[PDB]
Length: 149
Length: 149
Image 1 (cartoon, one colour):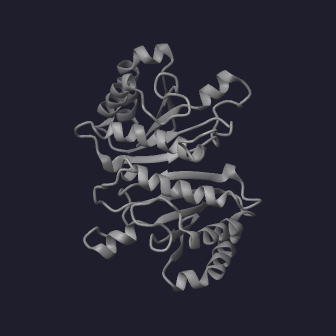
Image 2: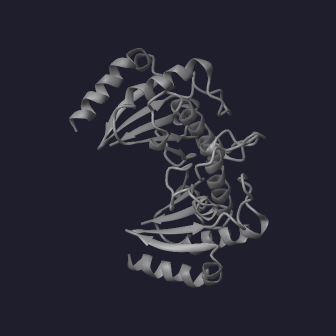
């Protein structure tokens, strides 16, 4: 587990500003490191299109973990509001596509193995917060990258 | 698992016909029941569009499992051939969207808990066989429904 702690703090350091700005949270979860990335500044609402300024952050994360063993699971999330858009068939679709964008962006980093990636759409099944206000529903719409040894 | 072993037989007998044809395969892996649906007959090649004749089979599976506890994880898979797609951005996308099509169909069944579902795209990271023949690749392109107690 030595590599877990060194890896976690290494990420914490490299992402210091993003963490301080609330755009990212990094915490240990059993034998996995979980990186949560807020919707604001990463995706436009209702869209899976990864936003320009966020691409490099994603690649940085990929850079940080490329030399570590273990599955990299990318998971998209929505709030519990039914979705009305013509582009996506449901919350499963949108949460799924968001994880797809991030995974596609990570595998562009040379040395980051494609084989390590797993993509998940979680729709509204794993809330962080009760869906009882706008601020909360927004925090639930994060994308998560889980590093699993 | 006795609730599972019963479940499994209920499934094996429910889908005996399709199990014969080779449309479905039912295995048991640990405390989990895996249903593998063959690409041919369920999805066109290169498409996440669930074929009309295959929809009722998916609903039937949702019916058979609606009464047991446990996560229902739907996973799409591809072979390792690069996707030549207008419609899909990558094998993550296509494999992902296939799992979305199946999940959306299952939750149309009354009493089936939306909250149980998980959607994953595995691309080519979990071959059942090496991608060295046309039969093998066709086989790798299945979709799986995993029932996890």
